[PDB]
Length: 246
Length: 132
Image (cartoon, rainbow over all chains, first blue to last red; front, side, top):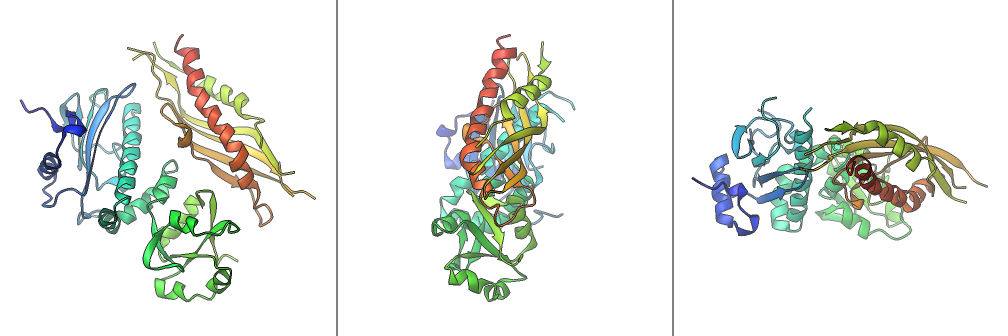
């Protein structure tokens, strides 16, 4: 009897219906932070309703978030390859018209890649709202960094979601885009420094020469960020330069 | 009936890519690798969900003058790529503070010609094995 929510038109669905559907499949007691409900048509046909939670689950990187349906028949809620692990925190449903039942599958790869791109569109929408992004970032910033570590195609887009303190963004974290806007036309590289903690990199003497040139320096105080940066290599055409390499 | 055009795509890129070029200058030397899939299947229609990874080798010079070498990786050339979709990982081999002008070169003049080429491939692929 019930026409599944994900087969309905996103434009017609109310926030309340999305909230009820999220609570139903997750036991969360909070409404979801954001919902990304879309349809893909053409040589690839599938629909999905994906939810980003307001908080990281207790066992995020430790201790069946997506139900996979094929032609509206539930198949499994534990198909990996549907979404990479750094996105394990996303919940919802994916309904494929074409996936072949019973099983390197090509359809699965296309679906997976399409889902990652759509979730990155969602993260960019979220970033446009500081109240929402604050919740998003504090809960999943590490997951974003791990995506940057491994996703060669999407790491540039993901890099746009990273936030860091800097010699010019001391009370708030800054984005890489805003660092770039503050750059004088003669500055060619984005500079950063690494250290064991904020208090120590904040007074490193290597900063003196950059400050004398009025060049902003980003503060990276964790190996996961350092690796994210060397995997990125550049941002919006500007090379990422670690000022303590000499 | 479906077919695997990975052999055709590979020679198509070898002639479409080698030689493209940007005092300061560079050009595509060879095509060191192309991996992934490219098939034209019958599904209603003659679809193709091709998705490829491609690396090209490069050579050029800035400045008397100073030459260099490197590679450019494009992780994804696919059936659903837009022009802005392509990613280019520019490597300048054993680089130096003087060579800091190669990449800006490659980004400004070579990449935009790389983008239009990848975009043409899909059309050419079907109008070669699809209208087939």
